[PDB]
Image 1: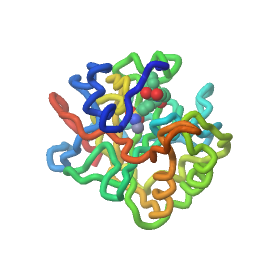
Image 2: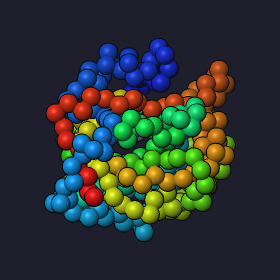
Image 3: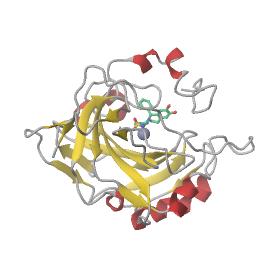
Image 4: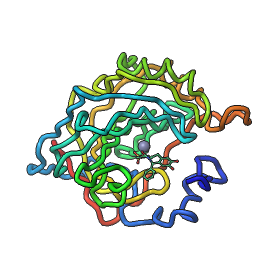
Length: 260
Ligand SMILES: NS(=O)(=O)c1ccc(C(=O)N2CCc3cc(O)c(O)cc3[C@H]2c2ccccc2)cc1
Ligand SMILES: [Zn+2]
């Protein structure tokens, strides 16, 4: 990806991605708008299982598109299973997408409603051995999406907010151990699910999306700190990292299922 130049600007944004990543106009692209009235309850959907008790965070990195909190996935620790998933998916990293204003920022939408941000907890199917091989499979990844709305502060997120000053620009990373992702989950695990893809290039169609119905609340100060990050690297013209979200894509031949 040393030649990648896609971004979220006017000249390299989502509308341009298809030129280097033709799958952008594929049959199962993400994100999508979740029409709550069209989504059908699926009684066969088993309960979702989120086991982050042994999660081991290692580092936080500004990759120029977002910031990723990375976990040690060399062992079966933080895993996602159940729900529409068959097998075990291991947590590798989480990141967010947010806007320049509270009225936008999420990638998925609910009845066209846009949230201030969206958290993505990325997991890969252990039957494929590693992340690189998993992304080449239709059921290689499971991403748990959680909407963020602005209101009361999320205590469990503050540790992330305070370390952002150390990774302001692209390429910067910082030690980030002992962070518990369980502090970022809402109370309920009710969710919608559908087959889709990564929302950033290479836009591979390797994701089973599980989007929680209940958003979490974060404070205006917390999201404000997110908006102080930079897309550019150190010593380059300052480009605030905001609106790093891809808009809803055509649902096409897909059905969104509800666990409730
Ligand atoms: N938004 S999302 O669909 O949840 C998503 C999931 C995984 C990833 C991811 O973990 N990686 C690795 C880091 C990376 C760096 C880039 O510059 C980039 O353009 C994409 C990624 C993706 C990635 C996924 C699959 C193959 C290669 C890279 C990114 C986004
Ligand atoms: Zn994402």
